[PDB]
Length: 183
DNA sequence: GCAATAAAAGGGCA
DNA sequence: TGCCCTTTTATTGC
Image (cartoon, rainbow, N blue to C red; front, side, top):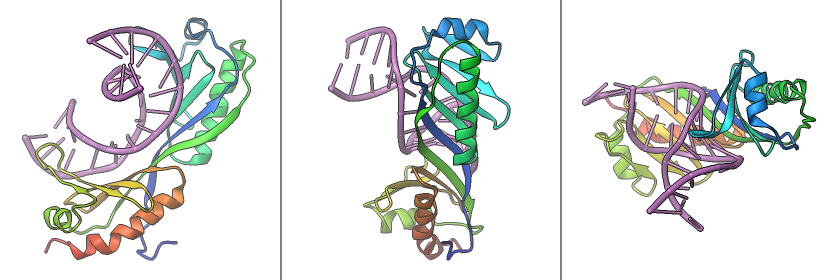
């Protein structure tokens, strides 16, 4: 499903799961060495494991957010590890409603892009204010994905719940990027 | 750095 | 209510 011949690399996956049990965040932050907590700043225990390299946000409600994985599977594995860490800490954690919430992929078309012309020709979807952010923000409607397009030809694709939406957004924009290649 | 992007979870605030 | 709290990742250019 890659007519362009380029496959965006998945860079970050954000997922959530329900441990399905109330948690004592202070007890976790004290029992765990690999855990940061200060409710004055944020309501979650921030934990990190080395493989898959991720960061979890564990809340008192038993709900948990997993960030930093390079794939959906790796995010699910990381999440299972935190839930087991939580269980070994004494809480009857379960593993329910695991869902992929956001997928960030990036790629390189390897040719310069004329961001102003592209923005202008696609005003309905584009936001280009280089003084604020040097990347053109392309809010695609089908699929509903947001792409950050840079002069260098590097592209950031975010907002997908499935990797296929990521791949399709890239394929949809490729013809457009080529059209505004900077010569 | 740090700017903006997307997304989730919660406590706090006006 | 709503919006930021924090975390992650790619990115260019100040």
